[PDB]
Image (cartoon, rainbow over all chains, first blue to last red; front, side):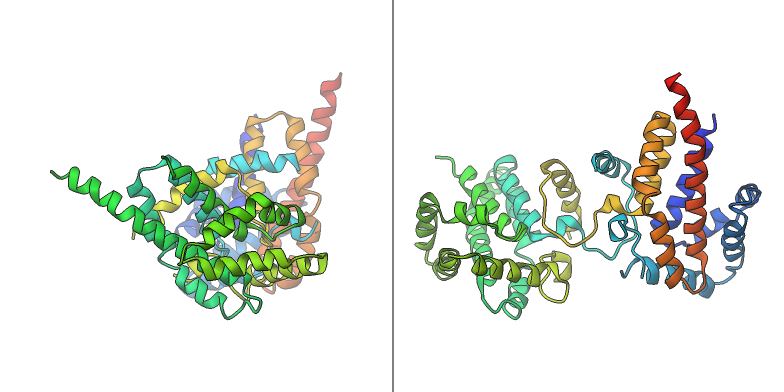
Length: 198
Length: 199
């Protein structure tokens, strides 16, 4: 009864922390239907001051420089770490419930953080999965596209940071292992193209 | 004979070495008598010899916690810092971006954990508020109340305090301030509503 309205307020607040505000969003936040909304929210004594600051700011963005500055505030405050909006930086089972929610919603926040699946550990773990669950062509393609395309660089920079050399050796072995695996996969994959063509 | 499962095991081993710092239990399983056989055999491949011997000589050389802590320090000061060799592909670089769609699914299913200093994505306030929005219409009042008191109201004021200190113009502080006041008023409505169902 009142819940859909509450969901709506939480969504709006969420959107404001999710990512910086672009032209399309600004137009959505300052339209007539949005103006009435902000007014209604302002009627509550505990919300009045905050609602006026938010609404007067958004209504004051008339050019590109105005929108760009607000975004700079967003980036300067949340994408540097500053006041990163992560609970753990200021302070259990309902994190898993959210984990699923995250996976389901396809809702991702603006972030300067590297993509988790871009972690070498993840790529290798996934390749291990491809070895027994995919065609050789998919395995080869993945090694050439996502692994062999950058290890050399990683290794190079690793040799300038690892004094001991343990992890430099691990990286070195990984590339060597990948190259040899690619050489075993090439003919296999090529046989299938010579056969699926004739 | 099928070698695909053997290849997967090797990729997993390499995966583990970048996945997290080596701990006591892991050092033991990486240096067991069965493991020594594996390394020796792997070292016989001409292309692998040098790095393998560096790998195992290092692992076999670990005989006290000091040396172990030293390796763990190498790991952290190399991958977990951020300036000097993060293991992320994007940081060193066509059908690339499209293969990331399947990895996310595998990453969600494998529930594989990579040691990291980055905060959890679900810990982000925007994701918590979106989740709360969801609970508002697909959950009992008590689950909503519980989540607010437990995950939001517990740290929001600390956040607003710091935010207010870094926000010169003050727009985002106003958003954060309105958020807390919204959450508090909502908890105020939720408590009476929930308590009543015990009657």
